[PDB]
Length: 342
DNA sequence: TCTTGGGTCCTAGGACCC
DNA sequence: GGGTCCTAGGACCC
Ligand SMILES: Nc1ncnc2c1ncn2[C@H]1C[C@H](O)[C@@H](COP(=O)(O)NP(=O)(O)OP(=O)(O)O)O1
Ligand SMILES: [Mg+2]
Ligand SMILES: [Mg+2]
Image 1 (spheres, rainbow, N blue to C red):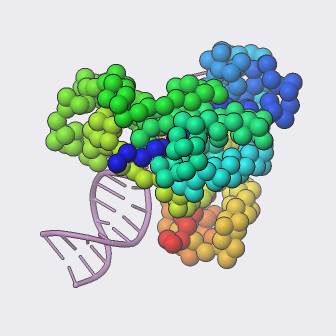
Image 2 (image 1 turned 90 degrees about the vertical axis):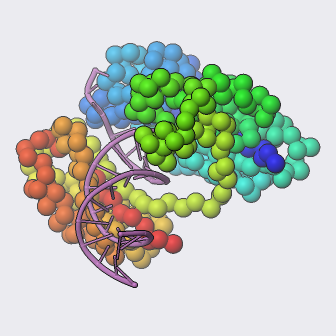
Image 3 (image 1 turned 60 degrees about the vertical axis):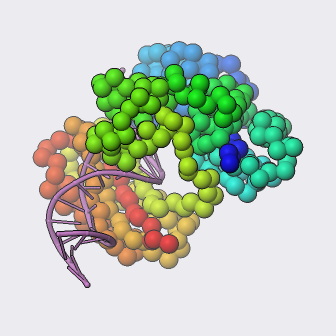
């Protein structure tokens, strides 16, 4: 009993929306991120700029060395939110089984769909068309019998393409597939696996589960299953935000608490406004704060608390500021809150 | 070049409880 | 002594 699962993913999402809204940006290298003097990274970049080596996560310092004519934008969320909202209403036309992973991505289970003679392929195509019409924005898709393979599949023919994997093709496909392409395995993990000869799913299939469990725990079991193309996770549609927070990174580090306090003052309204959006009474399960020093270590203190409170956050922030820091600069302060349990 | 801001989920020790 | 809450931290994702 195989399911038909689609992963959709908008191409170069933030940049695409900029370039839509300003055709002049179309053929020159642009990126959304915080400027160099702001100590920012790149959020995303268009293809002209990727050409040069610009990636997401890359410090803006490096983006500009690498691509000195890089036009840099601060980004417009309402515009990204608006677009997201539309793409989702578009998915809704084809199924209710929709699980968004971020503004620009969603899984659809389309198994029990009656939409295109039950052709997953035709469905993805129909959604990539209609997203283009309607948004002037391209999207790529992956189709597969499970979440992670549709995920990997949606990258394989991007931009503005799609790619299908049938159950027939799966074992071939997993044989040479590098563990790192599996969601949940990044740098650190890949490096461990490698260091013990494991690089592809292929290699994990020759592996003893008992051992994978000894040295990664619940992660070993995931690895092991995914290697076999096993992925039982259902598209759910019911997930809710569990927390919210707000953080800022100074252009220069701060060494005096007077400054730190100044920062927090500026952050609380923002974290109040966001939380009101979702909880007018301001009722939370815990609040707390976050500091990250010059040696880039980061620490957080967070306790049970019943209702967002500016003073308490300033309080605990001073404890923190005293009791852990020992004279390093401080690059960022942030606040945080954990939503009630329902 | 010099390392964001918004989140998720997993681990682990000690408190607390039957 | 075996679970569950509390808190801190880390790897990961977009
Ligand atoms: N590390 C990061 N930090 C901040 N914002 C980020 C980010 N990574 C992504 N974003 C924001 C900006 C991104 O536009 C958006 C979507 O994330 P993707 O789908 O991973 N990347 P995109 O759609 O840009 O390129 P592709 O064509 O390969 O899909 O999330
Ligand atoms: Mg995308
Ligand atoms: Mg994405």
